[PDB]
Image (tube, coloured by chain):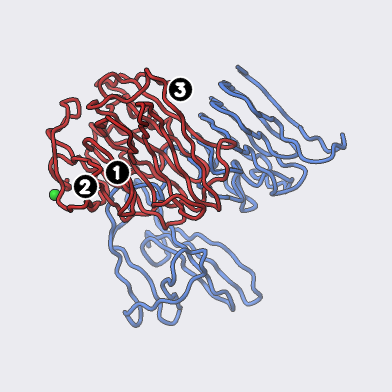
Chain colours: A blue, B red
């Protein structure tokens, strides 16, 4: 049992060790209860759990590790291990301040797919993102036996749900499909053009509980252009009651990500 | 292992965030298997009242009765479970459930078996073929852990690349036996069992000649991969119900019918 712990500035580059070492190695261990610890400012990975059973962590703060090489190391690395992690937090203070200091590529990495792990807590903190980054800036998915935040993994579920039908609309109203890269996991997708104004309209309106919208978009980027990736309502004005998420490309090739909101006067 | 006798409860219990199948109204997929046998007409015979239904599917070596799913195992893995009431007498191989068929370097197959020898000794065997090799993971049961003729058992496996477990649970006494294989226990991960080519079968494998079983089958479940952790947690709700309603792909009671 470790109750209350702080483990900081490991893998401290001036001491000149050769190689990467994590703030905490848990190797070949079992039945451990580790509550209320922090791992921060370490030069490599935060915690590496290897060949271990039944590691229980209740209240865990890992952030701003990987300080020896930006965007390279991970807060918790699992390798042939099982663990149950609750009350996880990890606000990356460097990403929040916009200092540009080297920090972890993200929270979790799975080096094997035979791990049985549950993780619950604040996996992405939700600060503004002054330099467009946050806690998890590189995400590597896993086929291991993972459950995170109690979320059902869509690849593993048979649950039946609603599935609303949108209406295709366009200058011509017949949809056209064109090839996508194979990382998209299908042969074709919907051809998006400014000429035809191809779009999908849902009749559903947004309510006070709010909404999540997502899509794979494969952009063709060239001259000055405004892409409307998705929207709520239309127009932009004191009373439009609308949201748009846009990529704006200028003549010189500068890209802006803009969110336009109109409403509430 | 840790849970060797499981006594289920009708308490207001939530374990591991799992939905208790007896308490749910969620709608799910429910894939339909095809019956196969030398005669392709299913036969149903009675089960013990502990099984909670009147009849189940009659399993015999002579007719090779089995249930074929067209679904193939994928890299995320699969769980398969059934009640089997085995009739145990002389030398015999029971193929409780299988992925694919055959057994060789390229068979891409899994078989869970109970092998009775001529002297009455029982062995539980997991046969893996693929990734260029084969492996038999088997053990002889001590006398006091042997399966008993005419007793219902819940029989379950979890199978994914690098991770195989099996469990056999007497539903009348709650006593369980099990093994789990990861890491250095496995010669290879057996990735090729899970390349979307090998289909799921209960009570035999997918080839017409395969060994089958003797006794009665009931309450066949196919789910996406569950840990033994979650399998055991779900047994505290009920010893024979589906493992995880959110991962359920098929569930067929088999009370004189292949429907639902
Ligand atoms: Cl029927």
For marks 3 and 1, give the one nearer the viewer: 1
Verify CB contact (< 8 Å) between mark 3 and mark 1: no
Mark 1 lies on a secondary structure that is loop
- Mark 2: which secondary structure? loop
Name the subunit of mark 3.
B
User: Neighbour class for label 3 at 10 Å: few (<14), some, many (≥20)?
Assistant: few
Residue count near mark 2 (Cα–Cα under 10 Å), binned few <14, some 14–19, many ≥20: some
Q: Which mark is residue B212?
A: 1
Badge 1: residue crowd in 10 Å (few <14, some 14–19, many ≥20): many
Q: Tag 3's secondary structure?
A: loop
Q: Are marks 1 and 2 on the same chain?
A: yes
Instruction: Kindly report which numbered mark, 2 or 3, lies closer to the viewer in this rendering.
Output: 2
Q: Residue at x 25, y 43 (%)?
A: B61
- Is the C-beta separation of discs 1 and 2 under 8 Å? yes
Residue B148 image label: none
- Picture disc at residue B63: 2
Front residue of B192/B38: it is: B38
Image point (62%, 37%), residue name: A76
Tell which circle, 2 or 3, labels the residue nearer the N-terminal end.
3
Please give the name of the residue rendered at 61% of the width and 38% of the height, measured from the top-left corner: A79
* Res. B158 image quadrant: top left
Asked where in the image residue B84 lies, by quadrant, the reply is top left
Q: Position of residue B143 (x, y in %)?
A: 38, 19
Gap between marks 3 and 1 measured at Cα = 29 Å
Q: Is mark 3 within 8 Å of ligand 1?
A: no
Specify the quadrant that holds the N terminus of chain B: top left
Tell me the distance, in whole angstroms, between the alpha carbons under discs 1 and 2: 9 Å
């Amino acid at each position: 049992r470790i109750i209350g712990g702080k483990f900081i500035w490991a893998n401290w580059q001036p001491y000149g060790t050769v190689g990467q070492f994590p703030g905490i190695t848990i190797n070949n261990s079992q039945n451990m209860v580790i509550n209320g610890i922090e791992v921060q400012d370490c030069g490599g990975n935060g915690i590496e759990i290897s060949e271990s059973y039944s590691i229980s962590m209740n209240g865990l703060n890992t952030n701003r590790n990987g300080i020896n090489a930006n965007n390279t190391f991970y807060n918790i690395v699992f390798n042939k291990s099982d663990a149950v992690i609750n009350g996880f937090v990890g606000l990356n203070y460097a990403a929040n301040s916009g200092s540009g200091a080297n920090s972890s590529a993200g929270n979790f990495q799975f080096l094997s797919n035979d791990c049985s792990v549950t993780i619950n807590g604040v996996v992405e903190t939700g600060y503004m993102g002054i330099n467009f980054i946050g806690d998890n800036n590189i995400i590597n998915p896993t086929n291991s036996d993972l459950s995170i935040n109690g979320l059902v993994n869509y690849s593993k579920t048979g649950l039946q749900t609603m599935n609303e039908t949108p209406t295709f609309d366009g200058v011509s109203t017949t949809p056209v499909y064109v090839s996508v890269p194979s990382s998209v996991g299908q042969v074709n997708g919907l051809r998006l053009s400014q000429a035809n104004k191809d779009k999908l309209l849902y009749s559903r309106t947004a309510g006070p509980e709010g909404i999540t919208m997502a899509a794979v978009i494969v952009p063709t980027i060239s001259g000055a252009e405004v892409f409307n990736f998705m929207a709520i309502g239309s127009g932009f004005s004191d009373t439009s009651n609308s949201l748009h998420l846009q990529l704006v490309i200028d003549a010189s090739g500068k890209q802006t990500i803009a969110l336009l909101l109109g409403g509430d006067g | 292992g840790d849970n060797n006798i499981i006594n289920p409860t009708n308490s207001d219990l939530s374990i591991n965030g799992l939905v208790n199948y007896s308490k749910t109204g969620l709608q799910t997929m429910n894939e339909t298997p095809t019956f196969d046998g030398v005669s392709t007409t299913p036969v149903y015979v009675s089960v013990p009242s502990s099984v909670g239904q009147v009849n189940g599917l009659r399993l015999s070596q002579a007719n090779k009765d089995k249930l074929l799913y067209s679904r193939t195992a994928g890299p995320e893995g699969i769980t398969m479970a059934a009640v089997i009431v085995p009739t145990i007498s002389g030398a015999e191989v029971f193929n409780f459930m299988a992925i694919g068929s055959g057994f060789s370097d390229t068979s891409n197959s899994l078989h869970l078996q109970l092998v009775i020898d001529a002297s009455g000794k029982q062995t539980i065997a997991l046969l893996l073929g693929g990734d260029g090799t084969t492996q038999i993971l088997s053990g002889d049961l001590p006398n006091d852990l042997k399966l008993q003729s005419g007793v219902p058992y819940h029989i379950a496996i979890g199978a994914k690349p690098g991770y195989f477990w099996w469990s056999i649970l007497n539903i009348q006494t709650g006593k369980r036996i099990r093994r789990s294989f990861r890491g250095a226990y496995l010669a290879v991960p057996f990735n090729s069992i899970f390349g979307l080519t090998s289909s799921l079968t209960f009570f035999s494998d997918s080839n017409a000649g395969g060994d089958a079983c003797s006794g009665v089958g009931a309450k066949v479940y196919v789910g996406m991969f569950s840990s033994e952790n979650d399998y055991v947690a779900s047994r505290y709700y009920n010893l024979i119900n589906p493992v995880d309603p959110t991962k359920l792909i098929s569930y067929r009671i088999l009370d004189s019918s292949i429907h639902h």
